[PDB]
Each structure stands twice: as C-alpha cells, then as structure tokens.
Amino acid sequence: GSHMQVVLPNTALHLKALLDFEDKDGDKVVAGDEWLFEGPGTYIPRKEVEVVEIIQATIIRQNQALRLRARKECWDRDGKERVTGEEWLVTTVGAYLPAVFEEVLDLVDAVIL
C-alpha cells in the first residue's frame, strides 16, 4: 500500500465509497459508490471507501477548465452520493481528471489577466 501521500502534482485518483446508506427520502447507497479525487495527496484508505484507480496530470492548460456532469446517479464528489443531475467543474492547471460516472460537456478557457 502507499498509505497517505502528499499533495500530488495536480493529479487525481478514483475512490470507491463502500458504505450502507439507507435513506427514506428516496436516495440511498449500498456499498457501491465511486468517484475521482483531485489532489488526493492527503487521501487515506478508510473502510468508508477504497482506492480504485489513479490518474496523473498531463492534458489541461494554465486556465482551461473542464465542467463535467454525472452520467448515472451514484458518483459522489465530496462523499455525497448525488444523482445524474449532479455535476462538478475541474479547474486544474495542466492535468487530467477523468471522472467515473461524470462525463465532460465542453471546455472553458479561464481568464489569465
């Protein structure tokens, strides 16, 4: 195992959230959630989730941003199993964060000056 690491060089890894979450509101997970993690340097393997895959940085620019939206309905970004309507935007400077259930919709050049 690599144990907790340090702020990666603008890279991210895919983690799988393993936990029994039963909610009567209409949304519940059963040991089967997974998502990408940018800058997981301080990420540690906790029973709650488990390291699934890893990704280095090498594709974005210094301002280009990538807005991605969920495709299924179980990929949690900050640990909150959201639905396909949930989406997140990546603002890395020279990297590449391929989500798992969230696909990209387009590109957005950020402002440098």
Image: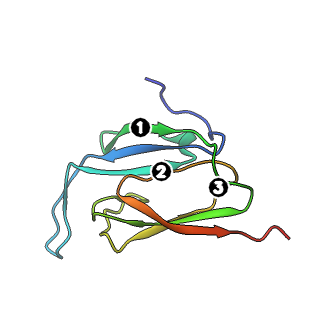
Q: Disc 2 marks which amino acid? A: Pro
Give SS at disc 3: loop
Outermost residue on the top side: it is 1
Give SS at disc 1: strand
- Nearer-N-terminus badge (1/3): 1
Give SS at disc 2: loop
Q: Which is nearer the eye, 62 or 19?
A: 62
Residue 2, placed above or below residue 54: above
Occupied quadrant, residue 66: bottom right
Left or right: 92 as drawn, with respect to 101: right
Q: Disc 1 marks which amino acid? A: Glu
Contact (Cβ within 8 Å) of mark 3 with mark 2: no
Occupied quadrant, residue 101: bottom left
Point out residue 10 in the picture as x, y percentages from the top left corner. 64, 45
**Can you identify the residue that label 3 sits on?**
92
Point out residue 60 in the picture as x, y percentages from the top left corner. 65, 53
- Nearer-N-terminus badge (1/2): 1
- Nearer-N-terminus badge (3/2): 3
Name the mark on residue 98. 2
Q: Quadrant of the C terminus?
A: bottom right
Question: Which residue is drawn at the image coordinates 17% and 74% (left, top)?
Answer: 26
Question: Which residue is drawn at the image coordinates 71% and 69% (left, top)?
Answer: 110
Left or right: 54 as drawn, with respect to 39: left
Point out residue 47 in the picture as x, y percentages from the top left corner. 30, 39
**Can you identify the residue that label 1 sits on?**
53
Residue 61, placed above or below residue 54: below
Q: Disc 3 marks which amino acid? A: Thr
Residue 61, placed above or below residue 58: below
Q: Which is nearer the eye, 79 or 109?
A: 109
Left or right: 83 as drawn, with respect to 12: left
Question: Which residue is drawn at the image coordinates 68% and 49% (left, top)?
Answer: 94
The crowding category of the residue bearing disc 1, from other C-alpha atoms within 10 Å (few below 14, some 14 to 19, many at least 20), is some
